[PDB]
Image (tube, coloured by chain):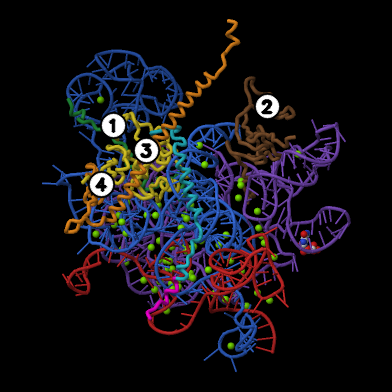
Chain colours: A cyan, B brown, C orange, D yellow, E green, F red, G blue, H purple
RNA sequence: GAUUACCCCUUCUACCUUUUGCAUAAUGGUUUAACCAGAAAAAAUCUAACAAAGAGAACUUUAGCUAGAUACCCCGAAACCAG
RNA sequence: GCCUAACGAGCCUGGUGAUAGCUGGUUGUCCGAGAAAGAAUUUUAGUUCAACCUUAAAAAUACCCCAAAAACCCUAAAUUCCAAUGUAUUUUUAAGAGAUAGUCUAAAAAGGUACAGCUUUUUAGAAACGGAUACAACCUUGACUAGAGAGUAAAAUCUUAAUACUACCAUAGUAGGCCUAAAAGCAGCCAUCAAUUGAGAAAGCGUUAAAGCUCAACAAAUUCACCAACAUAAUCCCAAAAACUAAU
RNA sequence: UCGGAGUACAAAAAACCCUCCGAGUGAUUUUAAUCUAGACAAACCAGUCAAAAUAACCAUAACAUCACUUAUUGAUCCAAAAUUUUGAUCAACGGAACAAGUUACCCUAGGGAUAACAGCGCAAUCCUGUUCUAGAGUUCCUAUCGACAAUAGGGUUUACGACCUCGAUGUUGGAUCAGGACACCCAAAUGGUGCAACCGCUAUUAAAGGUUCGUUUGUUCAACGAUUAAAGUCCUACGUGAUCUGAG
């Protein structure tokens, strides 16, 4: 090995914790999506005509 | 047939908490058919010979010298027949207590 | 076949990998303007870069690790002396002699 | 019972000729591994399957780079029959930020920083 | 299924056979036969 | 798959069912047409109303109530009973 | 037995859409994940719980895991438990069913015949459109679509078939002492000395006891010489063939 | 049904019409309280420990003990008791409040998940060879035999296993016609003999062709009469019932 057993202790514990914070955060964000007027109203475009 | 009734389920005798674990008072540390592990510091002995924690803390197993109670005939006999240098050793379970016993707080300033 | 030779010579075992055969932009406009880049080469760029970035990262982490250890050794050795400087002068046994 | 397996440390004490043979330096251990998954995890026990998954070795014949620290060497030791391990080499040194786009990894296991100038 | 020990010599799993065949003893072969030397 | 070329060449052990496992020499079918078999809203989830209250009476409520939408097959015994 | 072509109890209608843990059947397309059994049970042809699993939802740690640690006579492969580290998983909450008639391979055992494509548990694995001619389970292989590109994997005739050992020469105490009808080198018991350059109170055959053939002994010479070999089935043998032009 | 040891070698768990011991309670007085943190165990039901705090008692006094101590046990409902309880070889021991035979007169639903025929696996039993010689053979192991054992094959018998078939793979012996093996009964060619000759007894090679007629048995075998150059051993779904027979 390059490092000994004790030389690698916690040698990256900062990155590991960070990663897990991102994993958590990604899941915490899950919520039903926003609903907008452009949808419910935009449906009416179905019957659009020439006159 | 000749052979009968050998059928009974295991008793799940084992060691429940292991060295270095955290424990809360009243946790069963081990359960055993005969004494295998003896209770040490802050570990209570049940009447079925199971060991439970009397204190919140950390479990530790240890080898230590065995000096039986003089009210026990058998054990004192076993001890009495040993060659003059020999000492019985056994395995013990302790709980090294964690929280401090209590704190002093400021109630009222008169 | 002939992957063994190709490896001894330091190329890719498969002619498809990373040679000038694959990497280069196989067509161009007659005028000489370059062609829009190729999807394959784009992806290969991105993941080669990803790889490189990672190499950098691990190298740096291992270095910073070793330095942290050396520092901790120094702090320990400094505390061993921080005990002696801060110590009281031994009196009792020496004064009679 | 077929079980997991101990691997006596004597296996991993290198003989002085081995340095000459595989091209490692007697004095200084290399910094990084390029690990490749050479075999398949099928027909192997679940624990090797897991080790391969957590080494990023999922896809075959794709290189992956790992620290040469003992934490990693342990897992690698478990699956060493499923993989090929070769030391990463840096002739041109580690890449700066200008060199990230031009980086490439040659099969002799060496990372070239400037790829295809003009 | 057969017991571990048996009378009949017990055909091996193929991979074990390959092991056996690779690990056979190889006697050292002198460069010149000692008889044809002086 | 092809091929200038129908074959000739090459590659593929019908389909359902049942099974640890079916090319199976296990089940079923000559073929065509027409008929021939998943049904319910207690709790839940989703959408919406109004909200300490909601329901067009009767009830339910320590965010609930009201409404809507989401769900559970077909053929077959030997028998038994009455006239 | 017979009671209108089927009587261990007629026929018809109604009860009736009797009831079947048992068999059969169950109709558009495409996509996402995805299951082999612990417990009870008139139960083992079935259910209902667990464990897995699916759909949503909340979280936080989840595997992997170095010391340290877990028994008293002997005792293996190894477990348990846990930081670091590599990863992204795991746990709860709310809804759900299916499944619970199992195969072979390797390993530890038991039963049997140290028999089974046998049976019963435990650990692991598999169920290719590639390979092992054919092939479920062995081996290679993280299963997308289109190419009249490329690199690799496992993989295709297995070795042996071996046993030659020959010349030359033989006379002396003496039928050594015993037991026995006879024991003369050679039913048996005991000594095992001694002439000749050289030949045992004799290693095999032989005789009723001999006589008689050979061995070891001289001399004569001298390639090498320890062991090793093992019949067969019922429709018709079963690719064809081939000891060298360079092959990690 | 319950427990202890092995199986199950070191955390737990772990099967068998597996190997072995036990339990369905005694004896005794120390008559062994109330309430509650936390746990063990676990599908559920049941089981287990247990600090602190109360109350009992020396006036800061809570583990009934022994017999391997582990097991000495039983849910609901319902009955008896009146204050607080007791009640099942419900032993098929998760327990139906109370029910036996027989069917070849049988029926239906299924099952090759499971037997009888046949196949297949295997080779205990069976059959072949070789290996080894103590011994039989007056002497002499191997002319002819050969104990104790050894190695390997064959796949007839009886089993063993339950893998194909139960929406049918119709079963004993005959008849007819036979296909095949060789482990040869006859015919041919030889080696050895305890082969003089005639007979024989063994062994080698050879499978083109042959291998009878009757009395009794359903019979295959078997016994008997008469013969033959001989009246072979077997395999073919114990060949052959969409060719026959039907005694069994
Ligand atoms: N022994 C006993 N019998 C019960 C119990 N519950 C119901 N029974 C039933 O009540 C009935 C009492 O009538 P018995 O036959 O005893 O005169 C029996 O059929 C018995 O089985 C119970 O708890 N114990
Ligand atoms: Mg037991
Ligand atoms: Mg059990
Ligand atoms: Mg692509
Ligand atoms: Mg086995
Ligand atoms: Mg079957
Ligand atoms: Mg199934
Ligand atoms: Mg098949
Ligand atoms: Mg078939
Ligand atoms: Mg057919
Ligand atoms: Mg079949
Ligand atoms: Mg059929
Ligand atoms: Mg069919
Ligand atoms: Mg059927
Ligand atoms: Mg069908
Ligand atoms: Mg049909
Ligand atoms: Mg509702
Ligand atoms: Mg549905
Ligand atoms: Mg009735
Ligand atoms: Mg009825
Ligand atoms: Mg009638
Ligand atoms: Mg029905
Ligand atoms: Mg049933
Ligand atoms: Mg069926
Ligand atoms: Mg599966
Ligand atoms: Mg019952
Ligand atoms: Mg369930
Ligand atoms: Mg450890
Ligand atoms: Mg951990
Ligand atoms: Mg079942
Ligand atoms: Mg089996
Ligand atoms: Mg398994
Ligand atoms: Mg094939
Ligand atoms: Mg794959
Ligand atoms: Mg895969
Ligand atoms: Mg001589
Ligand atoms: Mg023969
Ligand atoms: Mg041929
Ligand atoms: Mg638990
Ligand atoms: Mg107390
Ligand atoms: Mg019962
Ligand atoms: Mg029961
Ligand atoms: Mg129970
Ligand atoms: Mg009932
Ligand atoms: Mg009768
Ligand atoms: Mg009658
Ligand atoms: Mg029927
Ligand atoms: Mg069967
Ligand atoms: Mg079955
Ligand atoms: Mg039949
Ligand atoms: Mg039979
Ligand atoms: Mg038959
Ligand atoms: Mg049979
Ligand atoms: Mg058949
Ligand atoms: Mg055999
Ligand atoms: Mg004799
Ligand atoms: Mg046969
Ligand atoms: Mg058998
Ligand atoms: Mg079976
Ligand atoms: Mg049948
Ligand atoms: Mg049929
Ligand atoms: Mg014939
Ligand atoms: Mg012959
Ligand atoms: Mg003849
Ligand atoms: Mg013939
Ligand atoms: Mg037969
Ligand atoms: Mg027949
Ligand atoms: Mg017949
Ligand atoms: Mg007929
Ligand atoms: Mg026929």
User: Are the residues at dot 4 and dot 1 in contact (C-beta closer than 8 Å)?
Assistant: no
Element carrying mark 3: helix
Q: Which quadrant of the figure has residue G168? A: top left
Q: Residue at x 62, y 20 (%)?
A: B85
Q: Residue at x 70, y 35 (%)?
A: B106
Element carrying mark 4: loop
User: Are the residues at dot 1 and dot 3 in contact (C-beta closer than 8 Å)?
Assistant: no
Q: Relative to residue A13, is residue H174 depicted above or below?
A: below
Q: Which quadrant of the figure has residue E36? A: top left
Can you tell me which quadrant of the image ligand 64 is in?
bottom left
Element carrying mark 1: helix
In magenta stretch: residue A50: yes
Q: Chain of mark 1?
A: D
For disc 3, the marked residue is C59
For disc 1, the marked residue is D20
Q: Residue F52 at x, y = what percent?
A: 67, 63
Please, which residue is most extreme toward the top here? Answer: C97
Lower sequence index among marks 3 and 4: 4
Closer to the observer: label 4 or label 1?
4
For disc 4, the marked residue is C12
Q: Relative to residue G111, is residue H246 depicted above or below?
A: below
């Amino acid at each position: 090995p390059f490092l000994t057993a004790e030389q690698e202790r916690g040698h990256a514990a900062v990155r590991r914790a960070a990663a897990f914070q991102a994993l958590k955060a990604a899941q915490a964000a899950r919520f039903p999506a926003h609903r907008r007027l452009e949808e419910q109203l935009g449906h009416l475009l179905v019957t659009r005509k020439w006159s | 047939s000749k052979n009968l009734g050998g059928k009974s389920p295991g008793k799940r005798f084992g060691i429940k908490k292991m060295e270095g674990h955290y424990v809360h008072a009243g946790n069963i540390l081990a359960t055993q058919r005969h004494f295998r592990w003896h209770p040490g510091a802050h570990v209570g002995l049940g009447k079925n010979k199971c060991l439970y924690a009397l204190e919140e803390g950390v479990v530790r197993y240890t080898k230590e010298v065995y000096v039986p109670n003089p009210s026990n005939s058998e054990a004192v006999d076993l001890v009495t027949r040993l060659p003059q240098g020999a000492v019985l050793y056994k395995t013990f379970v302790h709980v090294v207590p964690a929280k401090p016993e209590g704190t002093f707080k400021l109630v009222a300033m008169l | 076949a002939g992957s063994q030779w190709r490896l001894q010579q330091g190329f890719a075992a498969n002619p498809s990998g990373y040679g000038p055969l694959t990497e280069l932009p196989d067509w161009s406009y007659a005028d000489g303007r370059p062609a829009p880049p190729m999807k394959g080469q784009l992806r290969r760029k991105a993941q080669r870069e990803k790889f490189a970035r990672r190499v950098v990262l691990l190298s740096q982490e291992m270095d910073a690790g070793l330095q942290a250890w050396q520092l901790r050794q120094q702090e320990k050795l400094q505390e061993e002396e921080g005990k002696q400087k801060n110590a009281l002068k031994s009196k009792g046994a020496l004064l009679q002699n | 019972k077929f079980t997991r397996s101990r691997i006596p440390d004597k296996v991993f004490q290198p003989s002085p000729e081995d340095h000459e043979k595989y091209g490692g330096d007697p004095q200084y251990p290399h910094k990084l591994h390029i690990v490749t998954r050479i075999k398949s995890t099928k027909r192997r026990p679940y624990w090797e399957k897991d080790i391969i998954k957590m080494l990023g070795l999922e896809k075959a014949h794709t290189p992956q780079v790992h620290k040469n620290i003992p934490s990693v060497n342990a897992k690698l030791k478990v699956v060493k029959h499923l993989i090929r391990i070769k030391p990463l080499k840096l002739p041109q040194g580690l890449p700066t930020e200008e060199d990230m786009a031009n980086t490439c990894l040659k099969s002799n296991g060496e990372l070239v920083v400037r790829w295809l100038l003009n | 299924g057969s017991k571990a020990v048996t009378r009949h010599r017990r055909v091996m799993h193929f991979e074990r056979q390959k092991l056996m065949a690779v690990t056979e003893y190889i006697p050292p072969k002198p460069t010149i036969n000692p008889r044809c030397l002086p």
